[PDB]
Image (cartoon, rainbow, N blue to C red; front, side, top):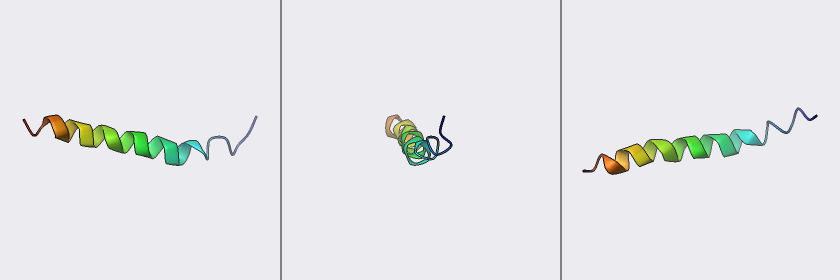
Length: 30
């Protein structure tokens, strides 16, 4: 359908993956 369609999920796929790492550290402040 579109080879570029995935190129847009690059920037949106890294951010959501970064916040997940920080979240784990948040609760670690226990």
